[PDB]
Amino acid sequence: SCNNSCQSHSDCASHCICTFRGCGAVNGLP
């Protein structure tokens, strides 16, 4: 779903959590 770096939903999108390890997806999606 979201495979990009970010700190505060700066690069993330579509309700994608952002952390030190970049953005995250749901249900293990691309």
Image (spheres, rainbow, N blue to C red):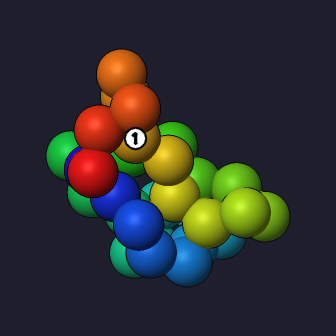
Q: Position of residue 19 (x, y in %)?
A: 70, 55
Q: Residue furthest left?
A: 14
Residue 7 x/y as whole percent: 65, 69
Q: Please say if 5 is above or below 1.
A: below
User: Where does residue 14 sit, x and y in percent of width and height?
Assistant: 21, 46
Please provide percent x and percent y for residue 2. 34, 58
- Identified at 50% across, 47% down, the residue is 24
Front position in the image: 8 or 12: 12
Residue 17 visible in this rendered orientation of the protein: yes
Does residue 27 appear left or right of residue 21 in this picture?
left
Q: Residue at x 72, y 63 (%)?
A: 21
Q: Few, some or many C-alpha atoms within 10 Å of disc 1 (few <14, some 14-19, many ≥20)?
A: some
Q: Quadrant of residue 10?
A: bottom left
The answer to whether residue 15 shows anywhere in this view is: no
Task: Point out the residue furthest to the top here.
Answer: 27
**Residue wearing tag 1:** 25
Outermost residue, right side:
20
For the residue labelled by badge 1, is the local secondary structure a helix, a strand or a loop? loop
Q: Nearer the viewer, residue 4 or 12?
A: 4
Q: Residue at x 40, y 32 (%)?
A: 28
Viewer-nearest residue: 28 or 7: 28
* In the displayed structure image, the side of residue 2 where residue 14 appears, left or right: left
Numbered-mark total? 1
What amino acid does circle 1 point to?
Ala
Residue 22 position by quadrant: bottom right
